[PDB]
Amino acid sequence: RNGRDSEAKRLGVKRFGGESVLAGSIIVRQRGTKFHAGANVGCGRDHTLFAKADGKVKFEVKGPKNRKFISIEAE
Amino acid sequence: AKTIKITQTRSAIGRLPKHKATLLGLGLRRIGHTVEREDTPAIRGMINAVSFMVKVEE
RNA sequence: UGCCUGGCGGCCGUAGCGCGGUGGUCCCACCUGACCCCAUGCCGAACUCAGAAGUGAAACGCCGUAGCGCCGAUGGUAGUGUGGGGUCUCCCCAUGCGAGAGUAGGGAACUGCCAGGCAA
RNA sequence: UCCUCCUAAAGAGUAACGGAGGAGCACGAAGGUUGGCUAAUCCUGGUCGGACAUCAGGAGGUUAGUGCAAUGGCAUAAGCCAGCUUGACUGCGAGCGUGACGGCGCGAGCAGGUGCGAAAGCAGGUCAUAGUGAUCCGGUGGUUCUGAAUGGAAGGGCCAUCGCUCAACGGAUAAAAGGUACUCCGGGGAUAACAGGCUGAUACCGCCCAAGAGUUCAUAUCGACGGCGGUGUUUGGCACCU
RNA sequence: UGUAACGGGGCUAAACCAUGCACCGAAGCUGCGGCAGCGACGCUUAUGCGUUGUUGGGUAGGGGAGCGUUCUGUAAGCCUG
RNA sequence: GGUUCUCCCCGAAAGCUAUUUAGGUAGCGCCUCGUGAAUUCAUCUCCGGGGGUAGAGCACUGUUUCGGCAAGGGGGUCACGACUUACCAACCCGAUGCAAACUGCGAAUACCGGAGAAUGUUAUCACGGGAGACACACGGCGGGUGCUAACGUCCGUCGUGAAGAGGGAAACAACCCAGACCGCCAGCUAAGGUCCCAAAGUCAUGGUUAAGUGGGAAACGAUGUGGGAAGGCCCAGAC
RNA sequence: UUUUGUAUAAUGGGUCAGCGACUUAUAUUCUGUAGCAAGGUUAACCGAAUAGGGGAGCCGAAGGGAAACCGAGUCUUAACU
C-alpha cells in the first residue's frame, strides 16, 4: 500500500560564502531557520533568506546557542 | 621556475574526464609525445594528477 | 594607576554547575507604606509610585577548591580520491587526504566604552 | 493529482507493483499590533482524592506545546494570556529561486489610504512545507471601450467574480457497457504457453558436529537442535533464442 | 555422443614465489614517400606556398565538392561508309 | 518491408517533462551549419564556502545482554504505631552491542564562488537553418529489489560497445592494451608472452611443490612437507 | 534487414536481362546569388505580343493598447522612485 511521494522542493543554499550577490537575490531556501538572517539580510515568510543590499555573502556562528547567521558586507 | 620536460607513456582512452582535461591542459596529445613546460606548483599538481600515465624529468 | 561597584557590548561552556569563604564607605539587593499614578482573569505576588529605618539572611559580585560538565594533543586505527592486484558477495599494494572514540594534559576565563565611591 | 521522511551515494535532482504516513481543510478568529507569561516528567505535605483532578515547595531545563501526518524550525519565543483592531488593503515592484512550457514561489522599495504603540517600528493573512483543475461555453455587478446608414439598444471587449471527486486530477465528446471457440487484418520472440539457455530458492544426493535411541555402549543400525557442499533428474525465478 | 575442468603435444620445471638482464609482440609510437581539412604567420593578394602547428574510425544525422546517363540551346558548327 | 553514383568534414541519443501515453509524438538535453561576443570555458595551485554520506558514537528516538543500588508488590512478627523477606520489580548507576526512515561527532570526493601561470584550432555563451533520438547493453564502483541467485530487474556515476578496426584472454560486441588518411619485404614498444604446434630465454641467482597440484569447488579431517617464535622434561641420564 | 546484440539455426533473395520508390502545383519562412533601393514589384488584362503598357494591389519605412485613442512614444495606474 506504499508508492506515494512528493515532488522535491529544491531547497538548500543557493549562494555560497564569498560570492557577490545583487539585492533581493535568494541566498538560502529552507523549511525552518537553519540559518538566521544577519546584517543586510531579510527573512521571508517561508524562512527564505534574501539579500537586502549588494555585496559579498558570508556565514558565521554567533549567539549563546552557536546558531548560524548569514550576513552581507558591501564589498 | 626552471626547465621541465614531460612525456606521455600510456593511452588516454578509458580515462576519466578530469584526466583527459589534465592531459589537454598539459599539451600532451599522443603516446611518446614530449612536451616542454616550466616548473611551477600549478604545473607540478597537473603532473601529480596524471603521474601514472606521464614521465617527468628535469 | 589600583581595589571595587553599575550599565552597554565583544566573546561565547578552558567561559557552565557543585562545595567553602568573603561584601555594605558608595553602588546593588532585600526591605516600610501605598490615599493618589499603575495592576492582579484573587493577592503591592509581579508591575508601578512615595521612602529610607534596618540588613548582607536570600539574590548578586569576587576569591579558593577539580567533585562534575567542558576543551584536548602526539601516535595508532577506521574510512577515502587516483592508479594497479587478489583465494574478488570482501580485501591488499603505491601515493594523497585523514577521522570518531580514547589517552597524557589543560581547565574553575579573557577583553572594550561610560558612570560613581575609596586610596592614590 | 498533491504533501513529509527514507531509499538518494554530505550542493540540486534521481527509478522500482521499494519501505513508512498524510491532504481534497480549518480560522473574522486560530489574522495584525502592543503588553505580559514560560512547559513535560518526577519527589515531599495536604478532605473527599484513589497511580493519575486542584494547592504549596523542590529537582528538571523543553523529554512540553506548536488546529491536522511527517520533517526542519521555534526562548527575541513561531508556544500561553489580555487590550485595541482589520495590512486577510489597492496600484505596482528592483532583483532572484524553480520549471520543456503552461506556470509556481520569495521579495526590498515607491504612491495612495489604514490598524496597533509614547516612539523606534511591525502589518500586502496564519511557524514553513499538502487543502487543488487549464481552455472553451455561459451567469452576475461595474465601465459610452466598441456598437457594422444615423441616435440608441442588443451583442462583444476590459475589470471584479461564479458553474466541473473534468480524482484516468496537462482535463481527447455535453453525452458510451459486454461476447466471439464463426472470427478477420496489420505487427511482435519488444511479450506468454512446449523445448533450449542462465540461476539453484525448492527438490534429490553426499558430508560436518553430536544430543539421544539402541539390554549398559553416540557412531552395528537410526540420529534431533544446527552447519557445509554436489547434481541440474521435480516444483520455481528470469524472458536470452524461436 | 568422445579424452573433454592447461587450447594440444608434452612438462618435475616447460609449475609456483622473489630479484635481475635480454628478446618477441598492434593498423600504438618513430623513419621514408604521397593525399586532404583547419588555424596562424613571411608573402602571393580570385593562388602557390622557401613555410608553421595540428587534424583526417564512424551509424542516425547535418555541411561541402563532384562523376555519369537521356533531352534543349551553342549546332545547317564539328566527327563519321 | 524496400529506398539505386562517388569523395571530403563534423558527429549523436536510447535521458527529463507531458501525453487514452508507454514500439507514437511535442518541448528541453545531446548533433550539425551559419552569425556575434567577453583571459567566456576546461584542467592545476591557492583562498572563501555550506553539508551530515563513509566512518564513529549511544546524549536523544528505538532495540539489546549482564551486575548493583534497589521505590514499589506478595507472604510473614507485631499494638490508629510498625516490621521482615528464601520472593516479583520501576526509575537510575557501571560495562557490552545494533539502526535506511537515531545523531551530543564527522571525513575523502563532489559542487558553488574568487585570484593566478601554462596549455587547448573559442574547447564557452547567445541567436538563426536542418536533424536524428526518447527499445539501450555489458563492465567497475555506491545501492533498492531478489536468495548479498540469474547474461534477472530498478536507480546514481565513469568506461566500453552501440557507432572502433588492430593485439591479447584457445574460440568470446560490451574484459585488458590501444583509437585504422594511404603506401613500404624499415625500426622501437603496450597488454600478453619466449620447450614444440607458434614470433621470442630449454636465461641467471635463491627457495617451495610429488599432488599432473599447477590445469574447477566448501565446512571439516590428517605424525604430508618448509620456515619462525617460544615452552616442559633431559648423561645426579629424557621419549 | 531489424536489433542492446547475428556466421547465426532470425527476416529476404534460384540466376540473368529489363522496369521499380522523396515528385508536381500554389502559398509561407530561412540561406545563397542578381537587380533596384526608402523604396521594391506588378496580377488579370490590352498588346502583329518572352517587348511595351497596366501600380488594382501587396510588402517595407512606427509602434503601444482589448479598444476608442495616442504617437517616438505608448499601455498600465488617481500618478509613477
Image (cartoon, coloured by chain):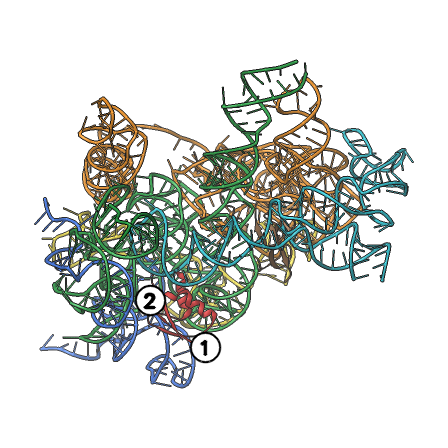
Chain colours: A brown, B red, C cyan, D orange, E blue, F green, G yellow
Q: Give the left or right position of residue C33, taking residue E52 as reference.
A: right
Tell me which chain the residue with mark 1 is part of.
Answer: B
Residue F155 spot, x, y in % from top left: 40, 48
Q: Determine the chain carrying the residue at label 2.
A: B
Q: Is residue E6 left or right of residue F38?
A: left
At 33% from the left edge and 63% from the top edge, which residue is drawn?
B13
Look at discs 1 and 2 and give the one toward the viewer: 1
Residue F171 occupies quadrant:
bottom left
**Left or right: residue D72 compared with residue G28:** right
| Residue F233 drawn at (x, y percent) | 30, 48
User: Residue A27, percent across and down?
Assistant: 58, 53
Category of crowding for the residue at label 2, using alpha-carbon neighbours closer than 10 angstroms: few (below 14), some (14–19), many (at least 20): few
- For badge 2, the amino acid type reads Arg
Amino acid beneath label 1: Lys
Q: D162 and A15: which one is in front?
A: A15
Q: Is residue G36 left or right of residue D146?
A: left
Query: Can residue A38 be seen here?
Result: no
Secondary structure beneath label 1:
loop
Callout 1–callout 2 Cβ contact below 8 Å: no
Please name the residue that numbered disc 2 is placed on: B10
Q: Which mark is residue B2?
A: 1
Query: Looking at the picture, how far across and down is residue F67, in whole percent?
Result: 50, 33
Quarter of image, res F174: bottom left
Residue B13 in view in this figure: yes
* Label 1 environment density (alpha carbons within 10 Å; few <14, some 14–19, many ≥20): few
Give the tally of numbered discs. Answer: 2
- Residue depicted at x 60% and y 57%: A58
